[PDB]
Amino acid sequence: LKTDEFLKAKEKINEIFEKLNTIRDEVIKKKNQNEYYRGRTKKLQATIISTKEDFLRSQEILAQTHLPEKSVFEDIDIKRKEIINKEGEIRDLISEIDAKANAINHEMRSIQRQAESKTKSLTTTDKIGILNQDQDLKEVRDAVLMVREHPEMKDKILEPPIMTVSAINAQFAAYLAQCVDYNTSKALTVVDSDSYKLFANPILDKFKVNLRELSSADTTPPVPAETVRDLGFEGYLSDFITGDKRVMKMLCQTSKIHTIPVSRRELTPAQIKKLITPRPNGKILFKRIIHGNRLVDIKQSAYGSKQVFPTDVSIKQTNFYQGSIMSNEQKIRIENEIINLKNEYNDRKSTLDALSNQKSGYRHELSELASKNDDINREAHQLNEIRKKYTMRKSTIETLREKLDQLKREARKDVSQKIKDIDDQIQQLLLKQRHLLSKMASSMKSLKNCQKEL
Amino acid sequence: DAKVIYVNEKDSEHQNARELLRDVKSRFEKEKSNQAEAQSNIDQGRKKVDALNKTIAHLEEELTKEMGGDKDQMRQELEQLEKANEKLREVNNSLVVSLQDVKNEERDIQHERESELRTISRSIQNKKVELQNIAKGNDTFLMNFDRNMDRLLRTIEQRKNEFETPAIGLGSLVTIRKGFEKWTRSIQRAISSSLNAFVVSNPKDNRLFRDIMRSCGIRSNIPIVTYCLSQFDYSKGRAHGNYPTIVDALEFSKPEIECLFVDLSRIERIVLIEDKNEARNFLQRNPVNVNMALSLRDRRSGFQLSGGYRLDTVTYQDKIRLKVNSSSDNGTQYLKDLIEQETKELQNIRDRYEEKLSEVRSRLKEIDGRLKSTKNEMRKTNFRMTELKMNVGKVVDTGILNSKINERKNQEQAIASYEAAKEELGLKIEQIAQEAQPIKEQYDSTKLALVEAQDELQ
Amino acid sequence: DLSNIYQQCYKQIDETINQLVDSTSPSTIGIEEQVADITSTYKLLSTYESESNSFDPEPATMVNNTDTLKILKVLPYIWNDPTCVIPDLQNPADEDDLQIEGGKIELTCPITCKPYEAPLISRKCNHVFDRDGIQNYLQGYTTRDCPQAACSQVVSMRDFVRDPIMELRCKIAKMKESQEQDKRSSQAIDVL
């Protein structure tokens, strides 16, 4: 009840001792941080003086007057439209050059015709073109262009004689019409009495044709006719035209082909009142004789005075003289030479085309050269791509201005706020320690108790 | 012994331990607060990273909005499409060089124009032959080429009495008898020699010609016939038929010309039949003296009904002197049915065959529409290459203001250094933890223990 | 027993009192009452030394026995001129110490011609000099006389007393040249 608790003095002194303790260490603990923050402030000062230098160190190159170029992009545009213009001009030039190259290729193809026709009678060659002697021979051309398709017509009714009984050349090709009569000449060469009618279907309704026959029955094979031709004739039908058993078997009794000599030395028939000489049967021994092309016929009559009746109408011929070679002394060129001079007529326009395509190539080369000049100019102005890079260097230093301003602003906020933060944290601690001391200032009240109240 | 103040000095024990008490906890707190500051710096830097990511995204937005970032994807296919345009214009070159031979094609086919005009020209010119003018210059009724025929009869006949032949000129004599008109033009192919003859029958009267010919102003030197005008029999060669033969077809202007024909042409056996497309058996049965029959289709061609055993196409001269004894009522107009069919035929050919001309014209229309489409394709390819040209012209040009990416990179290395500092202070926290505890335990053990018997006076 | 256990009151109150000035930043101003009241609480509680020693009748014996006697009125007016010496030396009876005069003062013992470090004083001399300034160089002579040739002082160091008064002055003057200059430097950075 009464004083039996003398330890109350110590009980009270304990806590106030711990309070005289405690806060004293927190004093310096909190004091510490402001020094490191001041060190950071010194770092800020160093950085911002560095930025002070950086202002001018940048501005020396951060002109902004060396701006992205005023009109270089317009130059880019105009030269690009220029190269598209060059491309269009090149397109037109190459199209026209191709057209003119084809134009000259036209002579390159047609020049074969003037070489093929460079012969007498406007054409003689071993190709199909020989039939173009007449436009109306379109029928024979079509006939020959399809005769070879059949399995055996090509070998049973052969192509026109000029291809199978070909004459030596023009000087005998004209004679071919009389060697094999003109009607059969532009017909097909029937081979036998079976080809007579068996093969009319392919061509008869389309192109003109004719047939020939022969017979040998009773007792007398062919009688001599070879050497009765002693009238100064040595050339003969079946050799100057390439005869063969493939062709001329049937002609022995249809066209009377046994009377067509060939003559180099022309002699007049007027020296003849002798060939009346009959064959032993009383009929004429001589049937027909020729010199040059003066063919003469012999015929028979069985009534009246029995007088003879020759005739001189003969086939066309080019010359009659007794000399040698080229047949023409007065002048050389004839109507025959117009389709040959077609060569010079082609050559005129051809030289014009050649020089036209050559100057077109000149223009093509000049256009390509201009385009490449514009391309090297484009390269010389893309070299300006580095001059854009000053604007990159200008921008990056410009961005460094932003970064240094941001650093100044953020650090200014950082240091200033922390200064007051630590100062106020110290200030509140200054109040806490003093209020704690004031609290202690009442503790000694216990001293007056105990020792004497006991 | 005396229990006295000897122990008082032990109070200094607590102060020695306190000296390190202050230091250990002060260091621990200072370095852990430094770690806290470092972590706050990490947070500050990290909160900028997403903002800077969005800032570089905004740079990409600027590129897209100014058309700077469009060509980066495109360029690698732009080159390929430029090569595609190159090969397409090569194909166009192949097509145009496939569109000039079509011009050679049109030239070659319209060579049919020359083919048809050459044939038509002569045929149309023959349309002139009805009247024009008569007599001295009648190039299709009483003349053909030379303006001297009348003088020939008064020239070569001047000394007829020296001829070994009775004569009056001799082309003016031959004429056709009754029958059918279109038979006129077949006989000349055989008797052309007698339509310009002046007959003599000895070598010298025949040789005087070539000399005296030019004396009177004519140069023609066509060959000559040998004969002597007289009349004789022709009995056992005629055919078994009533319809006229060539002897009947030809009129006896002079009966001696009958024997002339019989001798130099053997015409007495020949007959005439209007068309080839007609009976065959009458000629085929082959009794004795069966002979050929003639026929004509037009002025340019004919056919031979040669007994049926022979059928041949025959040719006749375009220009012919032979004429018929028909009256002069209206001449050709009495006959125009059989002339128009020979001239209007070619008009029908060109009218009907112009469909082939129309066919090639339609082919030309198709190929020139192809040409126009290829021209539009050239234009389209030019536009397609120009769009690529526009795309590659910009690429980036001057559209770069991205130094904030360099700012981002320096901030990235800055945050890397910040994390390095965070790890260094992570080492520091471990250092203080392993330094504080060994001394803190000693402090607490001593402080609690070293209070000891403090003031045990009694 | 119930005696002598309360002796530690002063022994720890000295620590309670001294540290306050050692921490309170001089940047904050206002000193007189805010030190006088709390320090007078010491005399209030110290009277109870005498009137708690039973009586072995009111508290006889003068209160001037405090070792912290001079701790009274230490901080005021000691900021710019910590060594507040007066042009007169022999007026200790009054308790104001600043009568009617002021002037200039010196700053050092013969340490290195540089300011005070650690004082010492004695009753016979009644004058203060530093600790190591009378033994470090002086030793070599068992006893050496007044600091200057035939000068005023009289010295016998073998029993000179330790002087804990002046060192309280030291740090305030030094730190003043830092903190206000630190404040000025903070202003200097503010304009950059």
Image: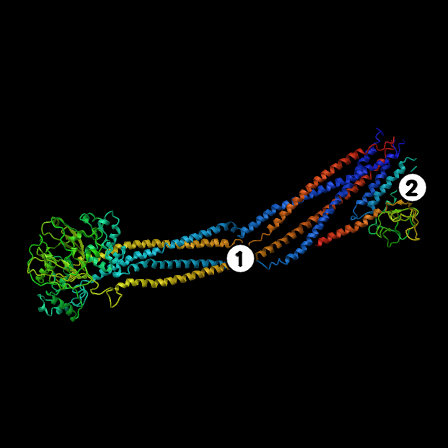
Mark number, residue C62: 2
Q: Quadrant of residue B330?
A: bottom left
Quarter holding the N terminus of chain B? Answer: top right
What is the spatial separation of the Cα atoms under label 1 and label 2, in whole angstroms? 105 Å
The answer to whether residue B300 is seen in the rendering is: no
Q: Secondary structure at mark 2?
A: loop
Q: Residue furthest bottom?
A: B215
Viewer-nearest of labels 1 and 2?
A: 1
Output the chain of dot 1: A
- Bin the neighbour count of mark 1 within 10 Å (Cα to Cα): few under 14, some 14-19, many 20 and up: some
Q: Judge by depth and name the residue closer to the eye, C85 or B20.
A: B20
Q: Secondary structure at mark 1?
A: helix
Q: Is residue A105 above or below residue C59?
A: below
Q: Judge by depth and name the residue closer to the eye, A89 or A258.
A: A258
Mark number, residue A338: none
Q: Are marks 1 and 2 in contact (CB under 8 Å)?
A: no
Q: Quadrant of residue B131?
A: bottom left
Amino acid on which disc 1 is placed: Gln
- Bin the neighbour count of mark 2 within 10 Å (Cα to Cα): few under 14, some 14-19, many 20 and up: few
Residue that label 1 marks: A382
B423 relative position to A15: left or right: left
Amino acid on which disc 2 is placed: Met
Output the chain of dot 2: C
B57 relative position to A301: left or right: right
Q: Residue at x 72, y 53 (%)?
A: C189
Pinpoint residue B324: horizontal percent, then vertical percent.
Answer: 13, 61
Quarter holding the C terminus of chain B? Answer: top right
C67 relative position to B35: left or right: right
Q: Residue at x 55, y 58 (%)?
A: A384
The answer to whether residue A34 is seen in the rendering is: yes
Pinpoint residue B396: horizontal percent, then vertical percent.
Answer: 54, 53
